Length: 46
Image (cartoon, rainbow, N blue to C red; front, side):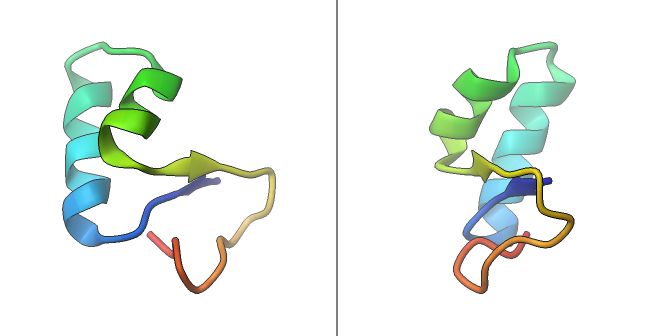
């Protein structure tokens, strides 16, 4: 899944996405990152 440091980062990432902006751009606007793994590491749990 998608892997964000904080709730606020998940929120911005999500707001970027909802306003139809592409995933990688939103990922770096937020500072999230993306894995295959169902759960993310302890530092990017959201």
